Image 1 (cartoon, rainbow over the protein chains, first blue to last red):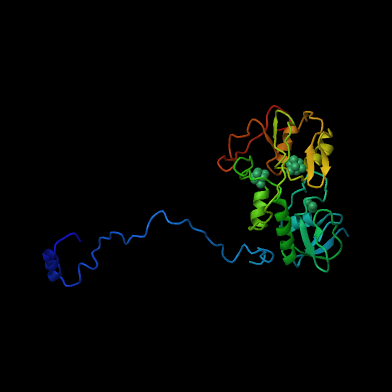
Image 2 (cartoon, rainbow over the protein chains, first blue to last red):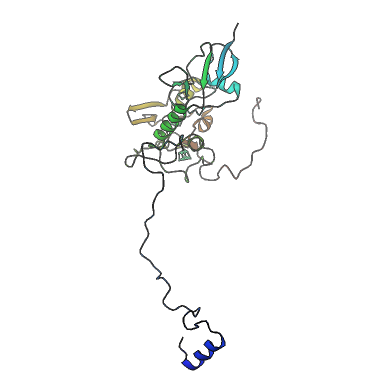
Length: 56
Length: 230
Ligand code: SF4
Ligand code: SF4
Ligand code: FES
């Protein structure tokens, strides 16, 4: 963005694909870094009393 | 005449009388995961890793001291055999510390190889892990007795081939310090052989102690000198 509407209309008239909508230069759509810290699962193991490795 | 039949996993073979299961399994090419057995010492049924299921048996017998009766059928790779090995390996890795980097038998442990090829992978035992105070057995043998699994191999070693009898078991239960009570230097000839008898990283070399690691070094054939025996 940060351009006037005259050259914007020239860009839209040079190719009609709504150039203001999808501009390939993202500003604050980026998800924020330094996220809340993750907790991670353990899958179909770590439940005790059955899981012999001889079985699986 | 001097021949007894076993079906080692259904494979029949003739065995000399008086011998036991493990010698028959090495006769047929099998191994059995073992700790306290050694092929130069006495047989003392302590390790319990050597178990094997025989058919028509409610228990699972140890493959060191059981004599070969006539016409066995030995299941080396049955179900509860592997279950028992997983159980006993999971017992062995409760009181053994996390010294796998700083130990001296990285590639040359036995706990590590047997715990891969026969042991479990998910552990238990959230709290505990006793610690044992080390001794100074001598300035030639570094000694951290916490890595000792009380496998009772150096004792029979000394009491037969050294005859010195300075290493004994002290205590009961979980608390069995194996060593010399009186802090005397265990020093005799063939004392250097004890650091290879020790199947874990508990009795190790003093001048070599933190200088190498077995996978980098290469082996080379050679003949002894300084002695007329070689
Ligand atoms: S010091 Fe080593 S050889 Fe002796 S009982 Fe302990 S683990 Fe076995
Ligand atoms: S003796 Fe084996 S299991 Fe124990 S710390 Fe050393 S390498 Fe690890
Ligand atoms: S060898 Fe049979 S008990 Fe250790």
